[PDB]
Image (cartoon, rainbow, N blue to C red; front, side, top):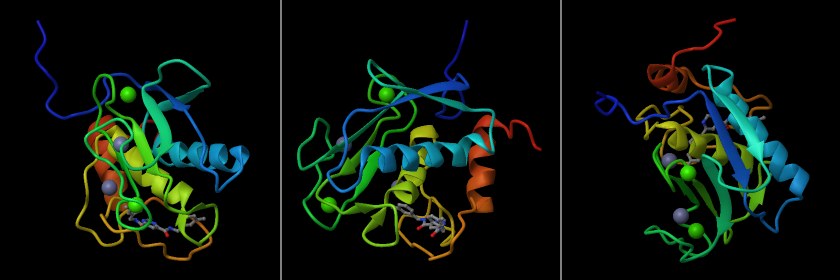
Length: 169
Ligand SMILES: Cc1cccc(CNC(=O)c2cc(C(=O)NCc3cccc(C)c3)ncn2)c1
Ligand SMILES: [Ca+2]
Ligand SMILES: [Ca+2]
Ligand SMILES: [Zn+2]
Ligand SMILES: [Zn+2]
């Protein structure tokens, strides 16, 4: 027999993702690079593997949309909500949605796609919000302006509590 796991998490280390559509704001290459780097943020500190699918059903379906887009969390035009992701689970679980009424960038203007994606994928993997103002999972977008990204310890401790550290070196 089997009882449901203690925490909400993926039961397999091999996860797949699919970029269903693209924002008008960035080139396909820029968007793909941003998401690849965002997934690497988490795979670098766990035993998780992320493989991209170009079609079909992936564990983490990524899409850009506006207003009503297929769930109970409609977006709201420019400003306000910017993105959301569902926790691990069947069907829409793990999916990540980005509000295309927002401005997405690979720089410091508007919302840095990589940064927001890293945050959203945290949710896709089982992390909720943190009270640490400097954590990636803090609820409010707080771009620091640093030239290099380093996953804050609070997030490292959080994701490893769910999946283990994988290779520690
Ligand atoms: C090369 C490079 C690229 C990008 C960023 C950096 C520097 N790092 C940061 O600026 C940073 C920001 C955040 C943060 O703002 N977290 C909260 C949050 C994030 C997204 C979405 C929501 C809703 C809330 N957490 C950790 N680090 C360097
Ligand atoms: Ca919005
Ligand atoms: Ca899914
Ligand atoms: Zn949605
Ligand atoms: Zn969040």
